[PDB]
Amino acid sequence: GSSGSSGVKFLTVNDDILSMPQARNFCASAGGYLADDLGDDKNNFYSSIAANTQFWIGLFKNSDGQFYWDRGQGINPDLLNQPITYWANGEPSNDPTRQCVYFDGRSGDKSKVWTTDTCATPRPFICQKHRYDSDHKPNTIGDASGPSSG
Image (tube, rainbow, N blue to C red; front, side):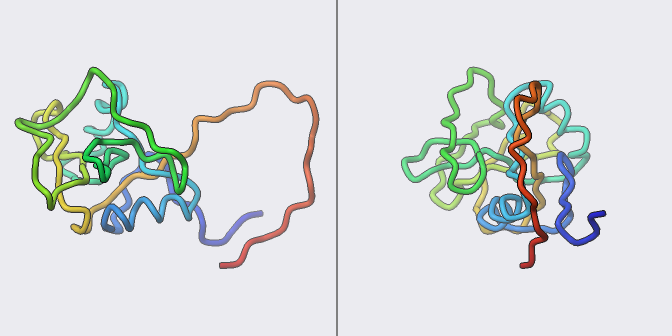
């Protein structure tokens, strides 16, 4: 059996408020990464759980000034090159203090939930696991594993 600590739920808003640079690091350590919001079926789903709740997302501005997607710790991020966006009225913003983006649940307009803000403000986030699955079983390639201690 497995009864320890590690066990962060996926696609779920974690009360524990943490800055962008604090959340992205957590999800990774736990075993996941910020849940990206690219696609209606994806947004329409968040808006629900985002019932008047503002949480961070995989959308974050980089040095250059472009918005990328969180793909874990170290992993190469993805550049926002999608035709569909949710940028609020005027967003993204051109403020030097605001670089990160957080889903605005309160925003009645689901199409205007995207909003840029400082990566220091403590806010909730959502961790997600890779979309990897198993299909064929060529070999076990397994090896006795042991417990972990932080």
